[PDB]
Length: 318
Image (cartoon, rainbow, N blue to C red; front, side, top):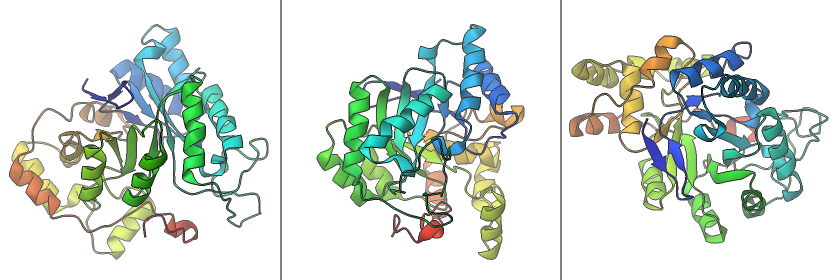
């Protein structure tokens, strides 16, 4: 129901359905199911390797008359091999073709990292393959060159709003100096173990909407192993989160999502189950108070789960 007005003039649903890590074999049906339930924003990306599957679910729902295209907010993200201005449109055309749509509502630069271009006929999506066997290889395309190509695509009608994912403050600040169309959205890893409060305040002060990912902190096998190795509890089991949930008669999941949604940050949880699907859609049924916000703020330990340093020592967050 609630909406964030982007600096581009369009309304972005505050609560969306996250397509990152969705089960491949049920993806189309979950998308359809989610539209039927009332979800309108779908947060996707070229790297998720499921945009055809998302487009088929979307297609089904539009065909049965449940929603019109203009009612949906489809986000995709430009992958790291496609930053050169010759190639940004090739990537975006594949997204649009996969999604079976004529525009996307939001197209983000996925990471400030420039992998060497790989033809889409060779491998798609390429992931960490950079055309040099198992080795990473990079190309010298400044962020602003990519941004200017995105701007061109906005003016060509293929994208409504553009933004960035996984940008630190200094890089976002420098982008703002060269941008003609300002970034509308900043999407970052955001949970009580990685709060980055000055980054949030910065983005919000410039009228940039913030979308959180990984609102639940560690969830994958690897992230929960790290957690155990660090003697750090999963957020669902964290004593502060459980105390606040108990206090409000709510689940830890609901406290985690509300923490963000109450501060005006967009959320895109994986809702892979009809129980989660309905709980995650009604997160705004209670308000955290000032003491809750103070208790949660103490949890910040700068624990970052999504770090290109881990890929190839790429210094994005250093």
